Amino acid sequence: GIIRTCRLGPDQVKSMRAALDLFGREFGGVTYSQHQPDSDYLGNLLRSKTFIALAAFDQEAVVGALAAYVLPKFEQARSEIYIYDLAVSGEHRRQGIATALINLLKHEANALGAYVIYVQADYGDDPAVALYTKLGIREEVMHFDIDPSTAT
Amino acid sequence: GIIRTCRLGPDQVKSMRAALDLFGREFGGVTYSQHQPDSDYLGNLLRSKTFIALAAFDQEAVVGALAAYVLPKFEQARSEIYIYDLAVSGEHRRQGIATALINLLKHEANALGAYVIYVQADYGDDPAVALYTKLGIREEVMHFDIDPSTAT
Ligand SMILES: CC(C)(COP(=O)(O)OP(=O)(O)OC[C@H]1O[C@@H](n2cnc3c(N)ncnc32)[C@H](O)[C@@H]1OP(=O)(O)O)[C@@H](O)C(=O)NCCC(=O)NCCS
Ligand SMILES: CC(C)(COP(=O)(O)OP(=O)(O)OC[C@H]1O[C@@H](n2cnc3c(N)ncnc32)[C@H](O)[C@@H]1OP(=O)(O)O)[C@@H](O)C(=O)NCCC(=O)NCCS
């Protein structure tokens, strides 16, 4: 029960595949565990300045993970970080794991001169909504999906 | 009134600064026109595979612009495109400009193997909401902002 948090680098594709499994198990979409990208693709993601993979380790086991994207802005020299997925092992809930990964993300943001971190949640994901409401400021917005298949 | 649409490259920082002015004027935030990043920063954005700047030209004038981010996914070898800003000159509305830039974005998505394009709107931006409702599928969601200043 000694938890370590870190940002994965491209030497850690093995721990990254294990974070992928955590997502699949926790979101029900094992979508995450078959059809995983090959090792070069994962390595290339971990090499980018614009993708942030964070993990919490129990021993060598991955018990929490967070994937976020850095969005370098165009109107001004500044950045925003967008949390895409965040999961914690079911056997490890209510132990501060999600909060520690978010805390590490803030340290990553500060190093990047990113001025805000933001994350989105569906109506009904009450854990998610409770966590983010404790940690940040809620706004409500609309999302639209567009199919590129219809290009003309 | 011959409109041309294209994706800017790093040789076109001049047209990109003009797209920045269109945003500032159209969103009221001229935030967009002072404090612009320097030319290397803009050039580096235009060099990335992960940032998409699209513009519509009347002569040499920029009359529409769209900034989007490609999000290479981690669970699977695939991508999503996230439209950040989209603006059209006030003297050029109701002429198909926004729709053409979105159409070009779909061609960019198809070339990238991106499978979806998505965009967000505030309750009350009825042009935006009407455009996106004609073009895609609305969902409603929550957004939370987190201040990295509080890292511990
Ligand atoms: C939400 C989740 C990240 C929680 O992780 P966690 O380590 O157990 O959270 P932490 O221990 O650091 O922080 C707990 C805080 O989150 C909130 N919360 C967490 N789980 C909750 C739950 N099951 N029910 C209600 N509120 C919850 C609370 O606000 C809580 O604060 P508190 O203990 O002071 O009341 C995750 O375990 C989960 O259950 N599902 C993943 C879904 C998700 O987060 N986002 C959508 C997937 S991308
Ligand atoms: C919204 C905006 C992109 C419209 O651009 P446009 O070139 O005039 O749009 P197009 O001519 O290609 O397409 C028109 C469609 O958009 C919708 N629409 C566009 N402007 C509208 C308006 N002012 N009022 C109501 N609906 C509008 C309609 O659905 C319309 O379809 P229709 O002509 O068949 O009824 C832009 O000009 C604007 O007014 N404000 C920018 C705000 C924004 O788009 N997003 C938030 C900023 S990031």
Image (spheres, coloured by chain):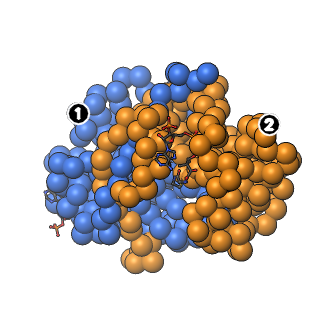
Chain colours: A blue, B orange
Q: Is residue B140 among the parts visible in the rendering?
A: yes
- What residue is disc 2 on? B2
Query: x, y percentage for residue B76?
Result: 45, 29
Quadrant placement of the N terminus of chain A: bottom left
**Residue at position x 42%, y 47% from top?**
B129
Tell me the quadrant of ligand 1.
bottom left
Are labels 1 and 2 on one chain?
A: no
Say few, some or many: other residues with alpha carbon within 10 Å of mark 2 (under 14 / 14 to 19 / 20 or more). few
- What residue is disc 1 on? A28
Question: In which chain is the residue bearing label 1?
Answer: A
Q: Is residue B74 among the parts visible in the rendering?
A: no
Secondary structure under tag 2 reads: loop
Q: Amino acid at mark 1?
A: Gly
Residue B53 or A17: which is nearer the viewer? Answer: B53
Q: Which of labels 1 and 2 is toward the front?
A: 2
Q: In the picture shown, does residue B139 fall above or below A139?
A: above
Quadrant placement of the C terminus of chain A: top right
Query: x, y percentage for residue A103?
Result: 38, 67
**Residue at position x 54%, y 55% from top?**
A70
**Residue at position x 23%, y 33% from top?**
A28
Q: Are marks 1 and 2 in contact (CB under 8 Å)?
A: no
- Residue B144 picture quarter: bottom left
Say few, some or many: other residues with alpha carbon within 10 Å of mark 1 (under 14 / 14 to 19 / 20 or more). few
Q: In the picture shown, does residue A9 fall above or below A80?
A: above
Query: x, y percentage for residue A15?
Result: 42, 42
In the drawing, does residue B137 fall left or right of residue B97? left
CA gap, disc 1 to disc 2? 51 Å
Q: Amino acid at mark 2?
A: Ile
Query: x, y percentage for residue B46?
Result: 74, 48
